[PDB]
Amino acid sequence: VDLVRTKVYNLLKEMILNHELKLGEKLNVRELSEKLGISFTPVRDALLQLATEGLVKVVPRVGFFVTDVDEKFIRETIETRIMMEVFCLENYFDKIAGSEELLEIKGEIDDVAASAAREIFDDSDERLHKLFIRASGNELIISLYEKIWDRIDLVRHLNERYVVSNREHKELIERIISGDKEGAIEKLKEHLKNVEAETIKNLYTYERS
Amino acid sequence: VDLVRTKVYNLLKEMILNHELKLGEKLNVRELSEKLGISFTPVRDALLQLATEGLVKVVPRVGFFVTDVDEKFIRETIETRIMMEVFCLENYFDKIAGSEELLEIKGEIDDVAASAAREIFDDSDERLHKLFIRASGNELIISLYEKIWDRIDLVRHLNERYVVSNREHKELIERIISGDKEGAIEKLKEHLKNVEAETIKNLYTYERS
Ligand code: NI
Ligand code: NI
């Protein structure tokens, strides 16, 4: 289920980022099905799920459309992350600082600063932000974030300054390892608000919206 | 859709609070359908939705069960509310303080302090906490809270100290109207953590869990 949604989602992201699909554009389910080798019903069901995260607009008896992602959609995405991630980092700080995972992410971060390989950025980016959430141990929280992860992920990709983001993550982690809880929190706010400003600026490079 | 889920949900709450249904108990869809005058499929679909909020456990090819609501389920519910509501109140404080709605809720609160009518408590309780969320103007946030509202509502009802909760709301609102933002925030944390401790204690009065 998550499995099909994730392939559907991944195709949709790939075609938005390639400018094959415009923001607001009507989706052709048959097309998606040809591309993915998945039958109609399962694709349809995935799209309904994505509509649930606000990625797809559903017009009954009409069809499915790619959301017309606009500034408000971005801002709301980021502000939602600030609320959740900051809440997790603040309250689960010791647990995050002490995790070995944080150290492996740090290693990826250092690789990006040298190589600038986007895939390693995406992996390290996801792991760091999700670590904050996961460290709560609060399965409701963690499932809320998971529920909107596809939206988070698409938004993540609508900017191009990943190397600067890489450096911001580095500094975050450094504050965290130093037990500078307050510094870390301010740095996370700063990083996300920075990402948000840059995304809003990049947005006109996408067809429509 | 929300319409059917809400009737299904309301019946389930009523029977849990009457101790007609135990926590963990297997649900009989036909029963629910007889009671509500709604057909099988729509009930089934509502139950699937409620399973989404973690109110119903789904066992495929077996059936649907009432969640075995335990301390962790309560704690996680409350901590999730603390994160969201505190984030909203802190960041949208002026907007909340200035709303006429807050004044009407205040009027209900004063009625409860005098009458102790549970329905007026529930109405005023819902409005106050939802005002914080709604004042964000962030439709993602507001939809996350709405998505788990049934869970919030059931949890709200698993304690019996609503008059004390009424007094805590009163003091909250008083802090808010006074522009004591920090006082208000601390009072909201305190209120929810208090509710949480009392609920955990009351919980053994419910069959199972
Ligand atoms: Ni980041
Ligand atoms: Ni309350």
Image (tube, coloured by chain):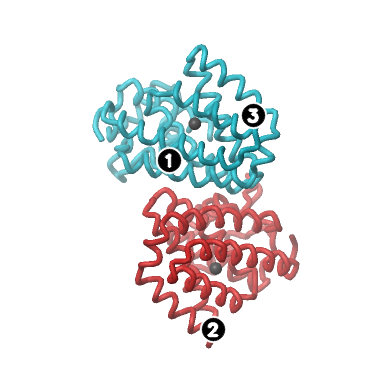
Chain colours: A red, B cyan
User: What's the residue type where badge 1 is placed?
Assistant: Ile
Would residue B66 appear left or right of A176 to someone viewing this image? left
Q: Residue furthest bottom?
A: A114
Q: Position of residue B92 (x, y in %)?
A: 65, 44
According to the picture, the residue beneath numbered tag 3 turns out to be B102
Callout 2: chain:
A
A51, B124: nearer the viewer: B124
Q: Amino acid at mark 3?
A: Leu
Q: Marks 2 and 3, Cα distance to the nearest angstrom?
A: 51 Å
Res. B76 image quadrant: top left
Residue projecting furthest to the top: B115
| Residue B178 placement (x, y as % from top left) | 64, 33
Does residue A186 appear in the picture of this structure?
yes
Residue at image location 59% in from the left, 30% down from the top: B173
The residue tagged 2 is A113
At x 55%, y 34%, the residue is: B129
- Quadrant in the picture for residue A200: bottom right
Mark 1: few, some, or many residues within 10 Å (few <14, many ≥20)? many
Picture mark count: 3
Examine the rendered structure and indicate whether residue A186 appears above or below residue B123. below
The residue that label 1 is drawn on is B78
Few, some or many residues within 10 Å of mark 3 (<14, 14–19, 20+): some
Figure check: B69 above or below B121: below
Helix or strand or loop: what does disc 3 sit on? helix
Chain that bears disc 1: B
Could you give the CA–CA distance between mark 2 and mark 1, rounded to whole angstroms? 40 Å
Of the 4 image quadrants, the one containing the N terminus of chain A is bottom left
Q: Residues within 10 Å of mark 2 (few under 14, many from 20)?
A: some
Q: Amino acid at mark 2?
A: Ala
Q: Are marks 2 and 1 on the same chain?
A: no
